[PDB]
Image (cartoon, grey):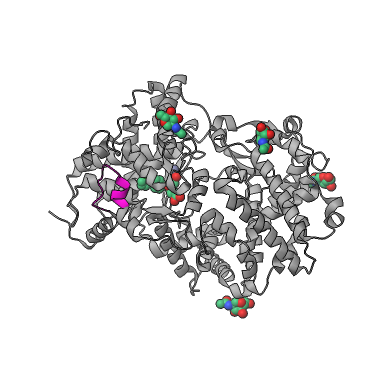
Amino acid sequence: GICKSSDCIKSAARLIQNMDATTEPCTDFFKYACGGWLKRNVIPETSSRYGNFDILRDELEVVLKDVLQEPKTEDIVAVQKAKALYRSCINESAIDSRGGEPLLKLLPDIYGWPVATENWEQKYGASWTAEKAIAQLNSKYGKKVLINLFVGTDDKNSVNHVIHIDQPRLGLPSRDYYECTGIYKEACTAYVDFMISVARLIRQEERLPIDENQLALEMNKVMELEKEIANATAKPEDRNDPMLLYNKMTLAQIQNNFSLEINGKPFSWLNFTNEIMSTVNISITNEEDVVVYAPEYLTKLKPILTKYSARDLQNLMSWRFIMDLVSSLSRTYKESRNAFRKALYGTTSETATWRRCANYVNGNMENAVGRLYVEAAFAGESKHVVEDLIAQIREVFIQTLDDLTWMDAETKKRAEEKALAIKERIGYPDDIVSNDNKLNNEYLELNYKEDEYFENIIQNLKFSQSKQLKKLREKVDKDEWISGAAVVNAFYSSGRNQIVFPAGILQPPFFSAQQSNSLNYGGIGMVIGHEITHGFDDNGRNFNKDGDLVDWWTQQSASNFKEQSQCMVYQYGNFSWDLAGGQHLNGINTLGENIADNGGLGQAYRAYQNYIKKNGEEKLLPGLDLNHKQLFFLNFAQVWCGTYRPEYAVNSIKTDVHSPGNFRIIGTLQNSAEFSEAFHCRKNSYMNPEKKCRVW
Ligand SMILES: O=C(O)CCC(=O)N[C@@H](CC(=O)O)Cc1ccc(-c2cccc(Cl)c2)cc1
Ligand SMILES: *[C@@H]1O[C@H](CO)[C@@H](O)[C@H](O)[C@H]1NC(C)=O
Ligand SMILES: *[C@@H]1O[C@H](CO)[C@@H](O)[C@H](O)[C@H]1NC(C)=O
Ligand SMILES: *[C@@H]1O[C@H](CO)[C@@H](O)[C@H](O)[C@H]1NC(C)=O
Ligand SMILES: *[C@@H]1O[C@H](CO)[C@@H](O)[C@H](O)[C@H]1NC(C)=O
Ligand SMILES: [Zn+2]
């Protein structure tokens, strides 16, 4: 009664090798599931995090290398363009021989970098306004500094786009880093040294004098400016109510309630919008509707932006771009980032060039590279099997609603509408395989020179930003996939109410028509549940079946929802993480993900119970004295075998909306009565707390 296929053997070995059978399952299921893997693996010098999930991403990269590095007769123009981009990217001896010159040529188009220009005021002062400086970085290069302006889907009207105004991102990973004490100190030091070093390299190249004390003073000014911007931005916890974030206005209204004075100007929102929007032949009047995500921030900016000169601001604005571009230049410029990378990620070296190149071209040519990938790696048959899993799990979710005693009947019915309404996307869009010419047309405006990597990425910057801006007066495309196919991940989009499962994720350990179904439900099954559940988390529940941000909850049901979910805030907020210096997770920032992990697990396990009930028990696995209910949980846990560099734990605990893997595994299993039964856990054993959190 034992499976002895080749596939069963591979499943078995992997499970056996990862686990540590000498830990007790009810003490620490993560150790039990992953202890073997932990004992045996070291984090590569180039990874900030390592583990089964990252290995999957590393192996996907290998496939990409194989499909990009070799020209073939039969290659369509779209594919040709992608391989050309790749070749430009991996030719380091061409890149190296150009030193910093490509960047130098670019510098005047952004109003220079004051610290590395002499007589900056003389050269740029008369013609410099915030409106145009900021606009330039935004419209031409996709770089958002100080004020973030973008075109995106209207939250309250999902068939349309609108302009958005939000707070910008920071050079360091989060606002927390800007306190610059304790765990953040080295990052602040590296950050300022990084600026110093780049300005010193550019000064050496242009043949200009170098006063070291001037560099220190000017760059620390940059940090002091960015420290004040960091302080002005809203915490992620004060941004997670999508209802309270959305503030539709007019540029008219915005000029009153949110005035600024920069270099004693003062600022013109209307000038600013047309500077950006003119980049694609669309002009704007005070009529225009504008969604404002950071009203408090704009207010907090007024007293700050009056204190700094054009030279002070341009120093930061430029640095924030330059920062991004430095790895794209010569070896000399590449080194300047070393300490900065180490302080944020813990990595002592950059990842292989071919790897960064594969990721770069994937990210800029997702349909072309997705096509190459799926032809090389993805079954295609898998698609129907996964389709049926989604139906089973969509089903379960709907049924679970009727056992929700805390939700009223009208809210129950409206939840069911959205569930039936969820659109799924599996593997890849067929277009990319079956319609060569359409794929060719997508990349029509792109022309890459093979020995001009930098010009290539600059061209890529403009093309992306142009595509995005030109959408303002356009209706949201329905058939558009929110991810390329060569991705090891999955997605839910509230704005389309759709779930996405790329080819990249439809492989072991998540999925294989050739692995036990206990593994399949435990893996991709859980992920399906996780993504359906996103439709209904602290964020998704605010969005209806059509992706529009409308309240469809009765006071009571919503209010009860918040009670149930308060449990998980406290559960996860009380996990504390050794790797991150004993800091505790943010139970609010990670709430949505934690809700989705917990929901997903229940649905996937109930679907597997349904499957056993409809089909009977599956053949056992050789070497493993576990039944299939236990195997479901094992595989489920081993998705997250892995570990973090302390540097990157410090980072991710402030920036990741997911809890760290160990804690996702602990948190979900602790809340699962079903887990403790499968594993026969003593009450109040660590894996089996008395209080259990439940929402879906
Ligand atoms: O790699 C990263 O940094 C994040 C990966 C990441 O979570 N992606 C998700 C994208 C998202 O959030 O919908 C898709 C996803 C992947 C794995 C799991 C899973 C599997 C087994 C057990 C548990 Cl407790 C969770 C749940 C969701
Ligand atoms: C890299 O650099 C230059 C491009 O002009 C040239 O000498 C050489 O052919 C290139 N090498 C490769 C492998 O592309
Ligand atoms: C940060 O912002 C708050 C509110 O505007 C204020 O109490 C304080 O002045 C700011 N702190 C620093 C160090 O700039
Ligand atoms: C914005 O203002 C400047 C002067 O401050 C002016 O020269 C320019 O025409 C305006 N830009 C746009 C895009 O209307
Ligand atoms: C930890 O749990 C307690 C009791 O549930 C709760 O009152 C407290 O706020 C939690 N702490 C965090 C940081 O979430
Ligand atoms: Zn998620």
Looking at the image, is 542 positioned above or below residue 74?
above
Residue 670, horizontal then vertical, whole percent: 32, 37
Looking at the image, is 134 positioned above or below residue 337?
above
Q: Which residues are the magenta region?
A: 20-34
- Looking at the image, which is closer to me, 593 or 571? 571
Residue 193, horizontal then vertical, whole percent: 66, 57
- Looking at the image, which is closer to me, 252 or 586? 586
Q: Is residue 518 left or right of residue 554?
A: left
Residue 462, horizontal then vertical, whole percent: 66, 56
Q: How many tags in the picture?
A: 0
Is 490 in the magenta?
no
Is 31 in the magenta?
yes
- Looking at the image, which is closer to me, 140 or 176? 176
Q: Seen from this angle, which residue lies furthest top? A: 556
Q: Quadrant of ligand 6?
A: top left
Looking at the image, is 649 positioned above or below residue 669?
below
- Looking at the image, which is closer to me, 114 or 682? 682
Which residue is located at x 50 percent, y 65 percent? 355
Which residue is located at x 75 percent, y 32 percent? 252
Q: Is residue 511 left or right of residue 345?
A: left
Q: Seen from this angle, which residue lies furthest left? A: 1
For the C terminus, the quadrant is: top left
Q: Is residue 680 left or right of residue 183?
A: left
Quarter of the image for residue 13 reads bottom left
> Do we see residue 112 in this rendering?
no
Residue 171, horizontal then vertical, whole percent: 63, 50
> Do we see residue 3 in this rendering?
yes
Helix, strand or loop: magenta stretch: loop
